Length: 359
Ligand SMILES: Nc1ncnc2c1ncn2[C@@H]1O[C@H](COP(=O)(O)OP(=O)(O)NP(=O)(O)O)[C@@H](O)[C@H]1O
Ligand SMILES: *[C@@H]1[C@@H](C(=O)OC(C)(C)C)C(=O)[C@@H]2C[C@@]1(C(=O)OC)CC2=C
Ligand SMILES: [Mg+2]
Image (tube, rainbow, N blue to C red; front, side, top):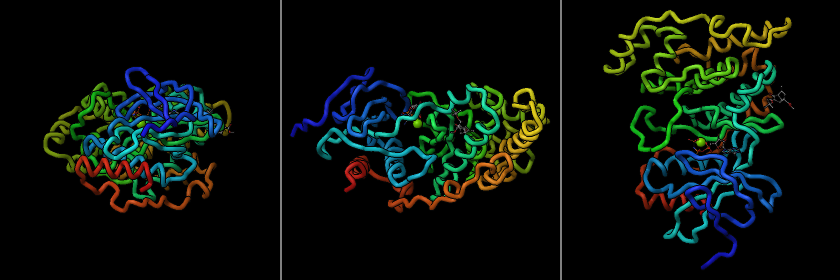
């Protein structure tokens, strides 16, 4: 039956059909997941972001990502993870079900924009501390992100930082992905881009890349393709040890081993004082502490790379430490088989439909 509670508006090519409470939709984002609109929620009396997922059950690749983002957004409640305000489908039946609409708080900026500003040590360390808190919270429920990037981290005018997405799940970070959209790889750890095993501190590499960018004002490892990405890492940080090499699959290993041998540059040369606030005693010490933290996160071999907990305890970060945010109880994920399931198209359609309905 027609439900008078919905209306339709065309945003670019695609149509949004939303509850009438959501007014004045404006497109703010696009990508592989779907279209994001800013809107005014007349019931909450605040601005929100509405993301449309089109036919998320269409194949398992789409379905696994949609499903886990629904489940996790609903069961996580943490200052540094984007919250779910609402979720709905305009279609009225399982048979007719097509689209899912995610409603989130509308944040004021993404971290790309925040990076463009000149940030003193207190602002950089606070934003990094918050990133570490959010990552630690995910890790505590066994969720390793693997794809953290500034475009998927947003910030509020009160300085609260929130991670927007939940990462690569149990997929291969060097397997083919059918998609028309560009995929940003600048922040992915060596072990991801070389197709190696990983552990929690895979996400520390990404934090290091973001921190270095915050300081320098440009992407640290802006590879124009997979080839270039690796080249840019080794040129700056040095060729990794033979022990690390022995982990690589034959084709990758021969390539990596036959690159020119780079010594790398010191973190003092990579991140000179000129790039930092450094007009005082506090600020000069802080620059050394920052380089010390970078030198522990931007480590190619993850077995020698610092952990999230160790980073939270680092003198650059720990000035902000509060166990209410840094030692929160882990998310309780209700689906005990999250990320361990293979399903047919119709099974995924019903799982995602129920998730929307809490049935
Ligand atoms: N809740 C939100 N508050 C503010 N801006 C948001 C919000 N959600 C998304 N955005 C904006 O949308 C941009 C990209 O959309 P996003 O939510 O990442 O999904 P997507 O574009 O469908 N997939 P992808 O680009 O691969 O991450 C971000 O850089 C933000 O600028
Ligand atoms: C705000 C922020 C900060 O990063 O602000 C933007 C505008 C995003 C650059 C901090 O990192 C902490 C908290 C602060 C603030 O005004 O809190 C009320 C200043 C600061 C050091
Ligand atoms: Mg995203």
